[PDB]
Image (cartoon, rainbow over all chains, first blue to last red):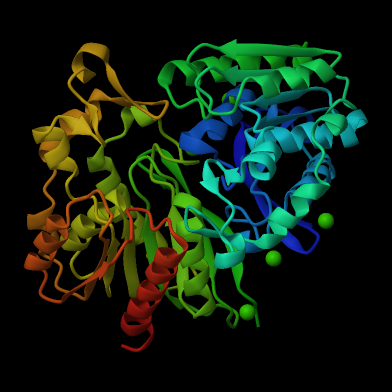
Length: 262
Length: 263
Ligand SMILES: [Ca+2]
Ligand SMILES: [Ca+2]
Ligand SMILES: [Ca+2]
Ligand SMILES: [Ca+2]
Ligand SMILES: [Ca+2]
């Protein structure tokens, strides 16, 4: 019998090494656990903001659910330059990470779910529709499903103009160079028609102080046969208040207990 | 022969597992390399913001300098609750990390330096002064040396009031609880009298848009026998523009080439 452990994991997808962390519950040798794979947001890292995914991972681990989270390609400690990042490759990696994680010794291939934050929720929704028979459930926090509308119609990315990409040669995201390839690839992305292909249990948690409009969470619900939408009064995009951090962890543990343990 | 590699490392300090990443250059079996140990800022993680420490780590690694960076206790993936965090224990961990990292198999303990960002620069400056023979050189980005003055004199932590910590039991830092122990421990901290004990090469990089007042960088320089201050026009606290990111990486590689590869 081995106590719980935190270990570091890697995988190779399309020639990039993706680097991640796994939180494995207490158990006997060779035990396979229900597992949540977590997708971080745009230009974020696998910890997410202010220990958010770390706290969620430990909460799951203490309750018998393994938690795995990788840096996407061109993010965090994974290989790849942000200038080469495209959302299509994030989607390819998210699908490939299902098989990478289900191959791990401690993961029950039949009790496996996705959790997302922000753009990671958008990726999770699309991967879930394309790999619907792989997922026991799907949980989406603060989904950034407005990102196509904002960039393509309002010509901004998180409020900053995208109209100087040709003049500058890049878009400046907090000191990272985001390339033209990202913007050229946006025409290939479909969120909601792909997302409605997943008809397992879905939970969406939206905070009223999120800068993403609430209507995008309702649009997801319009397409889900088994959706639940929780509106957290005065929650924000990253669950960056003490009360809303407790709320997001509790609501999510409740959902994964119901769908992966009960 | 071995190509460069990224490996994950852990060490135990005062009952907490601290978790870190090491970037090891290309080399022969058992080769040892000049090494930079990096200290992140307050409530940050070992990647620092927007890949900052990752980019610096890879730049060093590509040039034959190993880079090591841990989450401090109560930060990132390391053990410890933020409610229990104190700066004194950060200083103790920084001291213990010098010893743990100097014993790593790929580290040349005779060519070993610290790099800091923000509060990590303050920690680096104090540890460097207390362990004045241990470091080949010291580089500080955007040192947050105002933090005691801000909390103790202006009664704010990054602009938010600290006056309710005793009544309410904690301070809310972006969803994390920061306990009274942190605030009670501030009286134990001395920055500048400790920092001036280090007499090796020091480089400070300050951006004109940093919210930390420039005067604090001059106070450090006033106590350093062998200091250099670079002032980056339009640089900010976290080096969060493409031009200022290029500048900070280039200036720091230049300093570590001089102090770790050419000396
Ligand atoms: Ca246990
Ligand atoms: Ca593979
Ligand atoms: Ca690789
Ligand atoms: Ca090489
Ligand atoms: Ca431990």
